Amino acid sequence: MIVKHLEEIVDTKDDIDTKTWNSRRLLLTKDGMGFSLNDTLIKAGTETLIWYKNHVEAVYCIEGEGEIEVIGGETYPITPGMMYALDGHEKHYLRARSQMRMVCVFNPPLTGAEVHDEEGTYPLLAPISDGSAWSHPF
Ligand SMILES: [Fe+3]
């Protein structure tokens, strides 16, 4: 049996924060389910190029709006209830107009290494600036 809760996972080591996304890992390679499962927030206004050569991924949008553009393929608007699956290891752009909440399934599971290495992803456009600078302790 495995039981977890998103509200425990946030702001912990299984919550991986990147420029363009915040991935809350629900099932890890360690959990032995044969897939990994996460709840990923794609930050508003961002663009990320994605290419998983060594996994297939299912993505189920439960909040927000954006689009996925397949390289050499079509562009599919993302809205709540939209699902895409990269069974062809498609190279694609993932764009978030508003923040998107995505339930994602990877086969085989992603490893902690791969998530922290940001393997398979290339962040291209980060969220608009909130006026902060690294050199402003405040
Ligand atoms: Fe994707």
Image: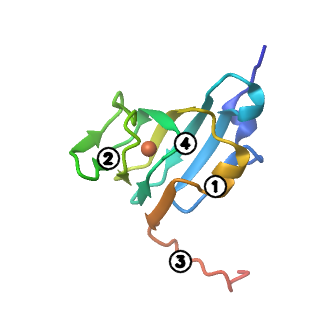
Residue 124 position within the rendered picture, expressed as x and y whole percent measured from the top left: 43, 67
Mark sitting on residue 40 = 4
Mark 1 or mark 4, which is nearer the start of the sequence?
A: 1
Q: Is mark 2 within 8 Å of ligand 1?
A: yes
Choose between 117 and 14: the one closer to the eye.
117
Report, in whole angstroms, how far the alpha carbon at label 4 lies from the one at label 3: 25 Å
Placement of the C terminus among the 4 image quadrants = bottom right
Residue topped by disc 1: 17
Secondary structure under tag 4 reads strand
Disc 1: CA contacts within 10 A as few (<14), some (14-19) or many (>=20): some
Q: Identify the residue shown where x is 39% and y is 60%.
A: 45
Q: State which mark lies toward you, 2 or 1.
A: 2
Mark sitting on residue 3 = none
Q: Is mark 4 within 8 Å of ligand 1?
A: no
Report, in whole angstroms, how far the alpha carbon at label 4 lies from the one at label 2: 15 Å
Q: State which mark lies toward you, 2 or 3.
A: 2
Report, in whole angstroms, how far the alpha carbon at label 2 lies from the one at label 1: 21 Å
